[PDB]
Image: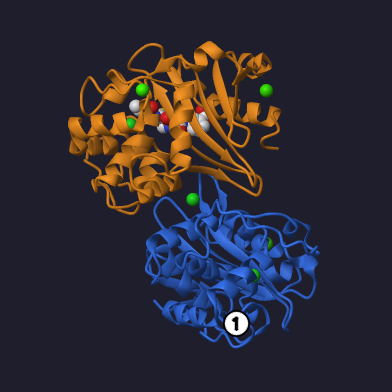
Chain colours: A blue, B orange
Amino acid sequence: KEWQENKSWNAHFTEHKSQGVVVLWNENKQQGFTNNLKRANQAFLPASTFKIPNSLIALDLGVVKDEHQVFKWDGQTRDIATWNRDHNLITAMKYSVVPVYQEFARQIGEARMSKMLHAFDYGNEDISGNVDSFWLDGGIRISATEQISFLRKLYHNKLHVSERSQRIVKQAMLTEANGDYIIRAKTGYSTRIEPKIGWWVGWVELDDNVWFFAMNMDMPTSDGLGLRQAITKEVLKQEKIIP
Amino acid sequence: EWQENKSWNAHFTEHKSQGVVVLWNENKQQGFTNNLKRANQAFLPASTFKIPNSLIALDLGVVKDEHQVFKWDGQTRDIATWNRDHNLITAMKYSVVPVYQEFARQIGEARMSKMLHAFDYGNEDISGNVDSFWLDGGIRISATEQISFLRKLYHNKLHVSERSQRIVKQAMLTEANGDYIIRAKTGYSTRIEPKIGWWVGWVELDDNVWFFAMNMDMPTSDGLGLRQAITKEVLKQEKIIP
Ligand SMILES: C[C@@H](O)[C@@H](C=O)[C@@H]1NC(C(=O)O)=C(S[C@@H]2CN[C@@H](C(=O)Nc3cccc(C(=O)O)c3)C2)[C@@H]1C
Ligand SMILES: [Ca+2]
Ligand SMILES: [Ca+2]
Ligand SMILES: [Ca+2]
Ligand SMILES: [Cl-]
Ligand SMILES: [Cl-]
Ligand SMILES: [Cl-]
């Protein structure tokens, strides 16, 4: 029923001297939960979490033929050392390799990008800036609860792209697996336009249920980046979702 | 070509056991093993047959997809995890035999045999009962024949739909972290001597995949964790995982 606040989760933010929101959705029970109902609906730039729809679109249109296709380094040295090599969809996702996804966006084109985001009902559906950086510094915006809504369609293969493309993106989202749970998720870090924030959105697969999640948090500097996952799983342990 | 590495035997004798580990570097097209004869010895697949059984069930529509629930038939059985409802993901993770015995009966002897010929799976022999031939019938498969089958699956080149193979590989997911992904399936063959345990699958890296297939003697069920334990120590020794 509706969305419950639960500001006790704030203690793991203040624990690590931080402020942000965490939003969970129980798929069996169709109930929501968050430490901050109003930050849950604040729309921000998606930054690198835009790689989920951008991969879906690129795959649906044939810009990416499969998760094995190699995407050649263009030769510019960039600060994140892992970007300066060849990549496929899996590794490009894993290392949030932006130049590979900018090339996808150029090849997709503004018209086909905008059409597809409307068909996804993705955030505010506005791609106002340049075609290869609007999700980093242009007009698009999405809330935490709007991330969940999108992810739920992807889990059920209900987005208007091919089932095969959704399966592949779901394979590429794989982050962690063990006897107790599977995590498919994607990080982000919006630096170009204030407020500097870091994202983590995905879902937990259990034997018998699925818990979707989406968090964001103030990220003045790059050294607090690990608290995106770390805090989220502290919430997850508290609600006994993961051991 | 195939290289023998007897130093791996330390991790078997560490644990009062004997068996074979087989590794295949996909980038370099070279395999390795601690025992070349055992590597090519054919045993019953036991529950590693759930990989092809799943593929045929999905390709023929016996299973719609990975979320379709399979009803507990009521009967209580030794392994507690079996006595509940399952989908494909959990039926594999817990090796729920009754669910797969049901798949096989609906697949039928004819289609099951045609598929195993098209998979070139082991000795391609399904003599015995429709619902148990992989436990106590005629089918046999070696560690190196498991590798060959799994490489086709990795590349989607088995004579079934791409969708089927993708789904089965999702269901094979076992472990994942920042360093590696293991997709794999266990087995434990007791109905016919020699009693043995299986672990077959592969390790995905950023830039390579290592296929593995191991089996070991398994006199009691208390050694079953050695399947993963011993494999992982070979992988550590070969610097495939940290
Ligand atoms: C024909 C079937 O009856 C037989 C087919 O090969 C079943 N398949 C399996 C199997 O595992 O393949 C089992 S054993 C049971 C389920 N899996 C074991 C396990 O995960 N054990 C486990 C898992 C993790 C750690 C440890 C340990 O000993 O430390 C042990 C416990 C069944 C008898
Ligand atoms: Ca805490
Ligand atoms: Ca050892
Ligand atoms: Ca043959
Ligand atoms: Cl990006
Ligand atoms: Cl089975
Ligand atoms: Cl997967």
Instruction: Judge by depth and name the residue closer to the eye, B85 or A197.
Output: A197
Residue B72 falls left or right of residue B43 = left
- Please provide percent x and percent y for residue B72: 25, 43
- A229 left or right of A124 in image: right
In the displayed structure, would residue B55 be above or below residue B231?
A: below
Q: Pointer 1: what residue?
A: A39
Residue B42 placement: quadrant: top left
Q: Chain of mark 1?
A: A
Question: Which residue shows up at 75% across the image and 58% down it?
Answer: A84
Check the picture and name the quadrant holding the C terminus of chain B.
top right
Residue at 42% from the left image edge and 79% from the top image edge: A119
In the depicted structure, whether residue B163 falls above or below residue B45:
below
Q: Quadrant of ligand 3?
A: top right
Number of numbered labels in the structure image? 1
Please tell me how crowded label 1 is: few (under 14), some (14-19), or many (20+) other residues with Cα within 10 Å. some
Compared to residue B36, the image places residue A7 above or below, namely below
Where's residue A69, x and y in %?
56, 54
User: Which residue type carries mark 1?
Assistant: Arg
- Give the residue displayed 63% in from the left and 77% down from the top: A132
Task: Using the image, determine if residue A203 lies above or below residue A193.
Answer: above
- Residue B105's image quarter? top left
Q: Decide if residue A22 is in sight here.
A: no
Residue B3: in sight, yes or no? yes
Percent of width and height locating residue A214: 56, 70
Q: Is mark 1 within 8 Å of ligand 2?
A: no
Is B107 left, or right, of A174 in this rendering?
Answer: left
Give the residue drawn at x 65%, y 49%: B178
Q: Which quarter of the rendered picture does the N terminus of chain B lie within?
A: top right
Residue A126, x across and y down, in percent: 54, 87
Q: Secondary structure at mark 1?
A: helix
User: Quarter of the image holding residue A160?
Assistant: bottom left
